Structures are given as structure tokens and as C-alpha cells.
Image 1: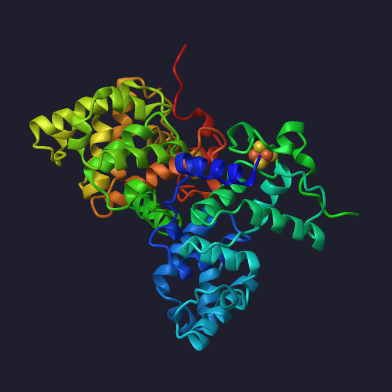
Image 2: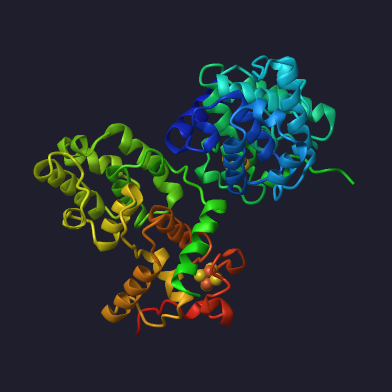
Length: 225
Length: 225
Ligand code: SF4
Ligand code: SF4
């Protein structure tokens, strides 16, 4: 499957099966996408949705979040777990208020420099909210690409991570990047699941090596020892 | 648990756990709620969402739906199953165009007279879209009320159905009815499930007879024979 076929297939699927009615998909902005990405990274969507809504109501802009006392932020976070995310969230908001005039930055290096934001989260923020042409590589994406392309290694190894980023870059289009990147996360979350993926429901099933060999359990590699 | 406590508990739960970002909860109208109720009645939400979106895009108003050829309606329905719903949908749209000037009716008797719309669907349409004070009684609601109140009988029997409607009427508030009725369906769909309900996550657990006796399997009564 040529990379142009991969993204065409994924975009066609997203058109007919995607949903873009999550609250961080309505009236999308860099702030909303960042907030949602941080919440989602160690929490399931069903649980995040009411927290997202409460945070957007209490903190309509990144400057409101920055000016709030940290204890109020932690209190609103209560129940999401992994509170280093909340502490980095608040620091990042403060850095946006201080360094960027309260306007969430729209260029990659400035986004990636925020506390709590890595390369994938920065490309997610800018691709999903502004259609900028960046690939992503969260756990969902890693599982889809590692299965399709038979990446055996543990992504905790630098060369394996690098191989996965190269594959992501290869399949990520510029045209329709916001749809493609949302679709890849939705696929990884709902279809290409950690256990017993639903390959018959997958738009990649015709080219996926794991599907061909019923070998999804091999990919990605797990932590060796 | 007094009925005023029941609806207070449910409304408090909905406030903190509800989500009102489904596409038929945004910019709600009688048309949108009707369409979604018909689709949902024999189809799971995950499957309905892309169909709802396609129907709203193709048919922004009930008059567009009425003027479309039936074959196009059936073709767009393809995959939802239970196509008598689609045939009644189109007839109902035509009856709205013909009898009600293309304005989806906002009074109970006119709504309930539409093909495909019963007493519960009519109260759902008007309560959810306009805050009118009508109770509902779909399968989700029946399961929550029958468990809470130990209604042993099969709701296919008229007296049992009547008992369930009386209970629904008793707990349904006027203030906050749109939230209460959405919350009761969400509870029945996600928490008070047909199998192994999640009672520890349920706002009624402190007064529910089924929870008290771990006897949810008895309620509602199943079809005798
Ligand atoms: S075909 Fe199966 S293993 Fe391959 S990407 Fe799709 S869901 Fe995953
Ligand atoms: S407590 Fe359990 S059985 Fe009772 S209404 Fe709630 S989920 Fe259903």
C-alpha cells in the first residue's frame, strides 16, 4: 500500500465513520486542542469530556487559566489522575501569558517549548486546530503504524521511535491533515485496540501486515526483559 | 426516596457526568430531536452519529426531507436497519410539510399524531428541544424505574406499562426537565445496563430496591412463557 493510498483510505473512512462533535472539535482553537490533548494523554475520552467542559467554562482563555491560583487548577483536575500534567498545564499557560501575550502560540518550536508538551502533542495542537502539516505519534498512532508496517521493536528504543516517526511522516498528508490525524487517533482508540483489534472494520486491513498474518500481538514490541 | 429527591439526585449527576455535546444536543430543535430519537430507537448511539450528521447535512429542515424522493431517504438510511422507521420518518416529514406549514409541531397531540411517533417519542421531542414538561418511557427509562421501584411485571402488559408511566410522571420535574429526561436515558444506556448494571456509579443507588437486594435481574419482568 503506497503512502498516498494509506492516507486516502484513512480520509475516506473518517468521512463516513468519523465524528467531529467532541467538544474540542467544535470551534477548534490551539488552546482547546492543547487542553484536550493533555487531558486525554493518560485518561479515557469518556472521563475527560466533563472535565474539559468544566475547564473551558471556568477558563475560557489561556490567560484565565494562567491567572488562576494553582490550587484551584489542581482542585478542578481532581479525579483525572497524573497531576504532573495539571502542574505542567498551569506552567504552560503562564508561559503563554508571559511570553506570548496570552495568545497561544501557533508555530511549532514555541508550542513544543511549553512544559508538558512534546513533539507529538505540539504537532497535534497545530495540525488539528490550524491544519498545519505536522505528523503525530501518540500511543494510538504507534499501534496502528507498528501493526500495519510490522514494527517489531519496542518504541521505547530510540531507533524504533525514529522508525515510527518516519512512517508517520510518510503517510501524513498536508491536504486534510486535520482529518487524517484525528482519524489515526480514532482508529488506534476504537478499532486498532491493544487487544483483539477489529480489523474487519479497519480501512487499512487490505494492506496491513499484522492483519495479513493475524500477528497484531507482535506489534508494537513490548518492553524487553 | 421521595420523588423530589429522585430528580434532584439525577439532575446533580447529569450536571457532573452528563455530556450534552452529541450533535442533536447542539442548537436543539424539535426536528433534530425527532430525527435522532427515531434513529436511536433501534440503533446504538455510536452507529447513529454519522447517519444523523449525513441526514442533517442533506436535509437541513423537515421540508427538505419531505420533498426528497423516498428512495433517496431509504438509500441514506442504508445500514441503520428497521426501515419501517425510515418510511414513517418520510411520511411524518410530509405530514409536517402538508399540515403544519413545514414547521415541526410544538404541541403534544400534533407531534404524537405523526407516523412513527408514540407517546414517549412525542414527550422526548418536546421536553428535550423546548423544555416542555413531559415524561418519557423508552427502554432505558423502563429499566431504571423498574429496578428502582421493583416493577416485576412485563412492560408488555398494559397495567405494568401504566405503572411505569405513573412512576415516570411522578419523578419527572418541570424545572430542568430537558436535563432530567436526557439524564434518565443516559443512565439507562450507560449505567443501568441490561446486564450487570454499574450501581456504584449510579446516583439512585441509595434508594434503588434492586440495588439493595442485588436483584436487578428481576426487573423489568421479561415476556412470560
Ligand atoms: S487492519 Fe487490524 S491490526 Fe491492521 S491497522 Fe487495522 S485494526 Fe490494526
Ligand atoms: S442502582 Fe443499579 S439497578 Fe438501581 S437504577 Fe442504578 S444502576 Fe440501575
